[PDB]
Length: 384
Ligand SMILES: O[C@H]1CCCC[C@@H]1N1CCC(c2ccccc2)CC1
Image 1 (cartoon, protein in one colour):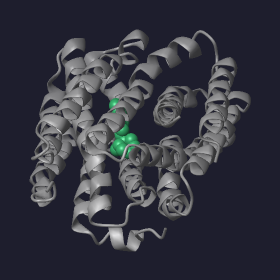
Image 2 (tube, rainbow, N blue to C red):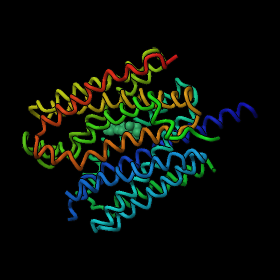
Image 3 (cartoon, rainbow, N blue to C red):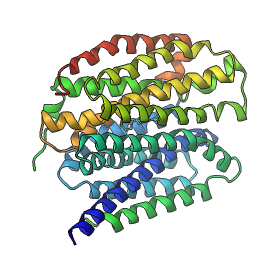
Image 4 (tube, helix red, strand yellow):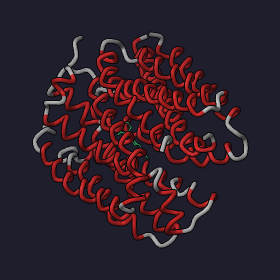
């Protein structure tokens, strides 16, 4: 029964991959579906979104050690449990402060669930040409839940309210957590004090910060830019993030296939992604109809797809080779990067586009990414 054992090992491993990708879908669906529905229930709302992400910046440098002290199935149980808590706290509560605590809770739940989920995808796929494939499918479900879910959330919020959508989504969350319990049934690490002084973790964390900063700044800012420049409406600005899903995954496929064909200069096909985000940093403020802004955001999701799918596998490869082979603290560093982007986002984005303008924010993205894109030369001989 050895070959039955190996096949069933592959079945449990693929089931854990699919279940963790669907948990990532549920979490990102929660995030990008509750972004529009909050201002029905009053400055102090940008601080709600950034308090989610800044709470996440609070808990994941602490959660990173608390993830590496334990097999990762239990800190994904914790993550989907507080996902269920936050989601029913959306569905039954309507006050701004319970909404605030639910969004914040979700911040800690993103820390636990997303960090341990990407971490056990990196564990359970130790071989590199299938690690990059599994992290690419993780990115695929994250982009699905972050891009095609605001259309489903719009069509089930201004046609079904918020009680029954978030209770059926809480049902899928609890069922995915209990299915993870049905399929998984659950040494010392590198300190963050020793990861933050490493140059290679620091340049990849700056890469994740800088590639997440346009999706940080634009998402509460694209709406008022539609209103000011393009004169948009309900049906227009809400599904202008949908058509950027299909390039994203396709871009993922490139930096999955090229992970196996030419794995030499992967940092090239990391930094190239950042460079085309710089193309986004040129092409966003000159869009004359719906199609140029759609293809600009397609390029934006395309570039961050390339950057995440080419820099999450080499992040686990970096903590494999240079450090001890645990994956909780290093994707806690990745999620600190994601979190500091989405925490600097909604506080300052709207007020600088009120004050300075929007071309100043696009040229700020240009200055940041074009002062950062040759810093990926620091990974020059790592791929050996
Ligand atoms: O930095 C990455 C690693 C940490 C966890 C998830 C992060 N990443 C964030 C943006 C997300 C995204 C956003 C918009 C469209 C498509 C996809 C892709 C995943």
